[PDB]
Amino acid sequence: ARVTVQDAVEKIGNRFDLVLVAARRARQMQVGGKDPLVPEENDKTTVIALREIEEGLINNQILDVRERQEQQEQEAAEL
Amino acid sequence: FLKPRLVDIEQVSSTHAKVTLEPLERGFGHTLGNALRRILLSSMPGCAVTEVEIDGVLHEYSTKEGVQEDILEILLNLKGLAVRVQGKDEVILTLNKSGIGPVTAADITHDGDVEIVKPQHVICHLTDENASISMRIKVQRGRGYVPASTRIRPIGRLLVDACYSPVERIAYNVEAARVEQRTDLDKLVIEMETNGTIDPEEAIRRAATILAEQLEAFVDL
Amino acid sequence: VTEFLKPRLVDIEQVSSTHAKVTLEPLERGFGHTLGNALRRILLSSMPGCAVTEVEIDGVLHEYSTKEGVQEDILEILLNLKGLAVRVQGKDEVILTLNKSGIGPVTAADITHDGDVEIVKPQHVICHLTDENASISMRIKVQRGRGYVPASTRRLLVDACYSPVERIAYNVEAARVEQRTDLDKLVIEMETNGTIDPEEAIRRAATILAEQLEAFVDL
Amino acid sequence: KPLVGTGMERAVAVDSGVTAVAKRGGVVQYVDASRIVIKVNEDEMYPGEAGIDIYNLTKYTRSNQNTCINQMPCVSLGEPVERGDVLADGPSTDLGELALGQNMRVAFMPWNGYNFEDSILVSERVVQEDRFTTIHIQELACVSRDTKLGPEEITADIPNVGEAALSKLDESGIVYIGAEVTGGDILVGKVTPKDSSLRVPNGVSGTVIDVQVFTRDGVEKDKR
Amino acid sequence: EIKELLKLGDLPTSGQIRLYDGRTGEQFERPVTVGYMYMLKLNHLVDDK
Amino acid sequence: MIKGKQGRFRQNLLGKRVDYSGRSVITVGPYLRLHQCGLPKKMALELFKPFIYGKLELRGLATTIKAAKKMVEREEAVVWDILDEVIREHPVLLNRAPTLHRLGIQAFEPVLIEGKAIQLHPLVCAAYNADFDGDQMAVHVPLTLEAQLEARALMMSTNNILSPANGEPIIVPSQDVVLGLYYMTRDCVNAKGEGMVLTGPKEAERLYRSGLASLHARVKVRITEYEKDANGELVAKTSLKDTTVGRAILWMIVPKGLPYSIVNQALGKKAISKMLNTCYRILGLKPTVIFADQIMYTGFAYAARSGASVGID
RNA sequence: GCAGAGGUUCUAGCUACACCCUCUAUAAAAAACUAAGGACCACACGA
Ligand SMILES: [Mg+2]
């Protein structure tokens, strides 16, 4: 649970790019079987996504790199 | 330290009674007084009326012939009526009155276990000579105040919200006692205003037991 | 109807050795404030503990003065001495004397034990001496008082904080069991001088309050 | 009664139509919750056909604002009543004095912010003694409409309903007078031609004081 | 006239009585104004809103 | 149909009536924190019905959505626990009917309460320009993850302390808490426990709660003042500062970074606004929010203790 | 389970937002179940 999102807003300056990146992360959590790297403690997907952003473990660049890598294994799976 | 004891119990009247706790250190007396007042007001064993069944009327709003006031007024008067039961947590009281004259609480047919604390209390007035009211009063032992809506069958049965609060006001004043060779000792005096269902000393004992049981959660007995 | 919901604490949160948080979830509607106020007032007004009440320093005899060669004013020294907390044995009163010289803080460790009495916090500082040649000499008096007795009500005198507690604040927040009306949740934050652990202090206060009520309950 | 009042409360209560005021002063031979009967004094009564005055107090009935109107008798048997005197207390009326609300002990002090700027804190004692419990009467009307595919029936039997809900209704399909109903329950059973049974609005919980059914001429009245 | 009315009763003429907190139990400093006031329940109930 | 207020533009295109909207009267609920608001159980049930149905299907309690609706109608126990899960971290928008400025609608993290009235945190009520007089606020529920995250990041009250119009904070204490702070931060020339030295704020609070020392009396106390002058670091300063017991008690509430000069004064409403502004500029948003909540609690408590009653005399 | 019908119930149930199984022209061993449509103008009142 996060009362405020400041740590995120200095993690992501725009605070609207923050919404987009953390929304994509939470979408990956709900739709994909992937789970948040930071442990979940009775927290919804958006809250734990903001928590992951807070630690700096997740950002827009890292998220784009991760999805590109996942598409790479998707291509490699077909061979 | 010194442990207070129920040195004196004084009854200025049946409803109003005073209990005194003579030996108490500075600070202990006022803390104990506030705690006892809150415990007594919050929760005490009470025997207020729970449900009333009227032979002649189905619901509380409609009125019966020959009765001065509405059935709703009768129910709310019965709410004020208070009884004390010695051995039964549940009891049924039956009221029958015929002819002109007020229907007092004394007229209620009472078992050996259940006794009406205030016979002078009036439920209704039967103005018409050929008017008779038959009531089945259900009294349940309970704690605190329960609204009628919170609880829960026949259409004739009427539910009145019960108030198992035997004590109306509890006032305590801290006055210094006069021990032969001692200092900083004060006697706690609690003024109890109650409908009379619960004994004052018994109520103090129950409140003390409840507070002690609650404290036993904090530290092992 | 005689039955009550008896609380079962879910956690005893501890931030430091001196400062702890205690919470009880179920309790009862209105019981939380009663218990919190009772415990708070009972452990402020009366707690078995020993603190410094009288001080004698050979340097000066007047409170509104400054001992030569000491950075701290004696009034500042009085406050630091008041802050000092000491555990004592069965004996009620003991006098402790120190004569220290040289530049450096006067630690609560450096005070002479002068008996089996032991100080809980050696790290605590009484005063600082600027000059090496200058020396400090103090007489300290401790009493096994019960509560906080100001010196104003009572040749140097210092207010005595006999009660080991420093700060307590009880807060009542809404709690539920299954689906039931609002039930008080009592959270108690207790800070102690260190002579007794805060949870042990709560247990001792509860035992005192129970002993006050042993007469009526009759087991 | 208002402990502090203008003094015009009596005038308002008397002039308002809710209060039943005796046409001719006299002694009350009989008083009842439904009606009050006055034996007129010989002087004030007419020389012929005066008889004795009878007043029928209206019981709990709906208002245009859904508030109960109830005249509670204000006099006892054998109590003389003078000319132009209040007989029974109407809504918000006590002893002929207009009594809109219940007065009570009031303390002006902030209390942990529960009365922040205009908020009001109320003791449990107020709820306990029913000082502000106000009877609200809501009228619900279900109308049998002539429609294509046959008129809609008023029968008790409804497709896809619980038997417990049908238990409250009578045989003819109308809830028993004096029954207790809650939100979602069916009061009167009506079936669309081929379901349309009237239902208690969610949240509303009360008892039915009375049920009145009006039927057009030429169509048979049901059993209820 | 109000002061005389209070003096006729036992109640203080000041109109302010020392009041004790229900929970803490410590009487409030600066005694508060306590007295009986007429209060109307408006039909604007919460459940309808 | 096109032009005017009744025209389709302003009626149904510019401002559209929306679903998942709940309306009820306002209540203070001082126990709530800044980001939390009271929300009735039935109101949250009605607003969050699709989420409840989804969670019921996931739990396997109801095999079909019709079964879930039947379960909700029964209002059985498991439905309440499901409602607790969804409400826990799902912000809802509290919105006063005339939305004069941007702060008119602000999200809150709902807390389920037994009742029928919405509780709004006292500090933000000044920002909402909302009294407690049958005032009603609409409650809209964000649905998508983008929406919930958007509300938490922007719409939430703690996120916007400063009003957009001016840099001055908008959650400034308004009626009761400001009065209590003023009562604490005052000096009486003679009062109980005057002229004694106090070790710290803890001792001041202990003296007041014991009642032997009056709330407002000039006493020398030792305070551990922290300075932000160090670059990204706090340095402790210990000194004996003449002050009242009330001010010393208030000092433990404020964060470390703020100096003692702000609390030393009488703390009128403008003074408290400046205090909050300095806290926002120095300590940051989160310490400012915590300090605002704590200061509201202390103001309420010490105003209740004061009993500052209005009287004819 | 996407075009229809049948089945153990209760006229009808083929995903209609909608609940189970079968197949591409044939009807039953089987328990939880069912309904998706409707404005303006005036008055008064609260903010
Ligand atoms: Mg308003």
Image (spheres, coloured by chain):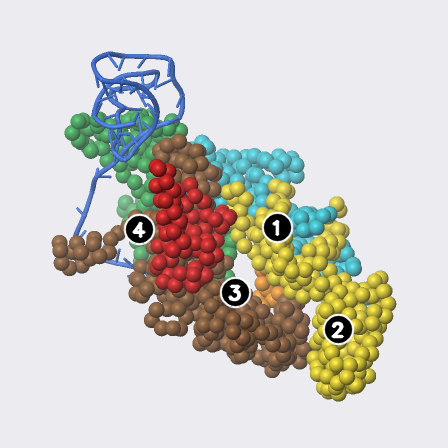
Chain colours: A red, B cyan, C yellow, D green, E orange, F brown, G blue
Using the image, determine if residue E24 lies above or below residue G12.
Answer: below
Using the image, determine if residue F256 lies above or below residue D159.
Answer: below
Between marks 1 and 3, how big is the CA–CA gap?
Answer: 23 Å
The answer to whether any part of residue D102 appears in the image is: no
Question: Residue C203: where, in percent of width, then height?
Answer: 71, 54
Return the residue at label 1: C11
Q: Earlier in the sequence, mark 1 or mark 2?
A: 1
Name the residue type under label 2: Thr
Do marks 4 and 3 share a chain? no
Return the residue at label 3: F294
- For ligand 1, tell me if the residue under mark 4 lies within 8 Å: no
Question: Residue F238: where, in percent of width, then height?
Answer: 63, 77
Do marks 1 and 3 share a chain? no
Whether residue B142 sits left or right of residue D42 in the image: it is right
Between circles 1 and 2, the one closer to the viewer is 2
Chain for numbered disc 4: D
